[PDB]
Amino acid sequence: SNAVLEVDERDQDDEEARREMARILKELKQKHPEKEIEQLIELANYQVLSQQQKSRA
Image (cartoon, rainbow, N blue to C red):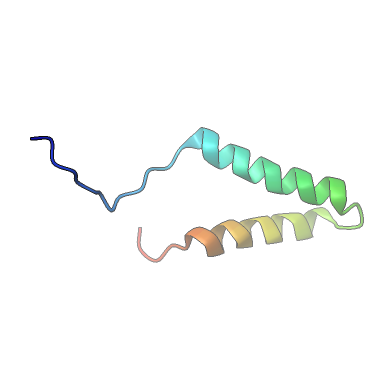
């Protein structure tokens, strides 16, 4: 028998996380030329923090 099992654990990668942050920053900088560097770092960190969310380390 093989038996099917499911895990409730998630893994994080440096290549997938770096490509995701580079896609949101390149799309807001090329589309929104009237936005400053302060508004780009505040909306980028607030979007990845609200989607993943951290309570305990």
